[PDB]
Image (cartoon, rainbow, N blue to C red; front, side, top):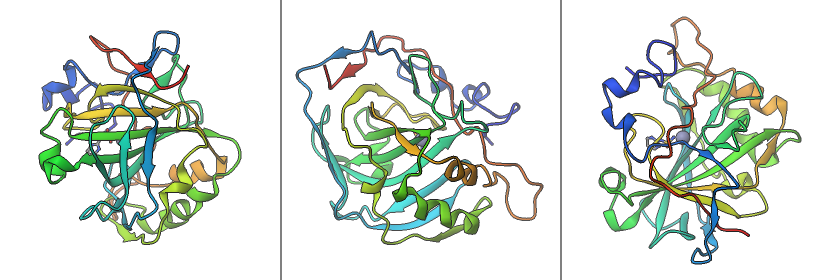
Length: 257
Ligand SMILES: NS(=O)(=O)N=C1NCCCN1
Ligand SMILES: [Zn+2]
């Protein structure tokens, strides 16, 4: 099964998932000079005041903070999107070192990590149907740089000891994802894919320009997680990022001048 190692990592995924070489794969490098301001875009509406977090899970690839998506409670609207997208989970990608870890890059710069808030289009009724559609998902991507601590991340960091290994989960109610957002909602957007198998080409990506700052100690605790299950030899969960993929026939649009 797929992973991030030399024998099962990104260069191998195309054998089981041929769409890995498709026309709208993610992530990509965002060339800031080539992206074009689009005055047709609207501000992003991020409405997370009623979000209901439930659980945090180590799935062997990353950890997911899961939300109750049985009602419009935490939704993304506006920007490039038509209609309403419900938050289902967020997770991160990160490196073994502070100079790598993001999936998207900005003028080839790698950030220490990247947060993905995953939302599905409510017109398709749930997530499994949404992933079969070209406009099924919207992923809000936020870069993490190492600097000052992000207070709203600390509850996540402090629960990681309890989900060290693959398949472990813990209650994670009453978490407010508003505390993971930067001040500005300026963004880039393009049509892409999931960055993990099955790599489905269902995503409108919305990548914020402003990174959030996290402390070195916060990201160090991400790097103490394990890819392996309990009782198995320890494999640190680091470098769980897919590199940039060919842009092919796409244009990245900017919401800002
Ligand atoms: N990293 S990612 O693009 O968000 N890929 C995902 N794969 C499975 C479903 C949700 N997300
Ligand atoms: Zn992701």
